[PDB]
Image (cartoon, rainbow, N blue to C red; front, side):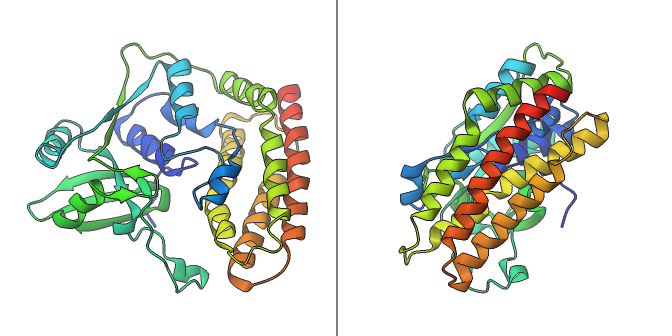
Length: 308
């Protein structure tokens, strides 16, 4: 496990790892101060990523925050097999790193056997990685979200960047952190804006919506939603850990139950993974834990604005 920037999703992980290595100001703090939750019932029933911090793979709300706070744009470069690797060489020569969208089917970033899951189904999902080296017949990539690196054959790398996925077709997409006129934001301004937006958009209500949909899965023999949910909610654990780390670094005033809320989310994840793999009939229990944390998160957001 590499010491890479975690962010709260593969997109923010890649952006922050890039910003860390290349000394790009503001990006890391804007990521670490994010506070968000979404729920898409239509995506739930399509076996797509349906909850957690953000819809993806690109986090459009984070891009809006980067533009609004730092006047930072994340430029999407689409390419072709004729041009993509040459463009990579030009970027590596100048910057030493290129942010790329890859089909995770061709990556082996997370060891599921560590959690006693030996039936590891390959899926065509877009995932952000950082290209660090182009050789004749191989590339080196860092997956900062999963703290993993690998050497990939040029053949497999090209396949991973031209692949049809569950979310659509990758076409050698690469991402450039660009600014013409950056701005500095204080960490308290970033958190104030995020917590006000969380309450105004009633994002805690999306947690309740998620709980209500879980309760209605008691008769669903297809438990894949619980595995998807488990993976989706890592983003929420990471935002809670990021806010704990901001509190320590900036000596911030926080409501006293932040660690308890992180523990509540970790337990919800543990129960979803157990439900998925152990065939338990405890959708009501998991629903109850989710509906409880929704109420606690509403109160926590109100309290942050009072003490910050």
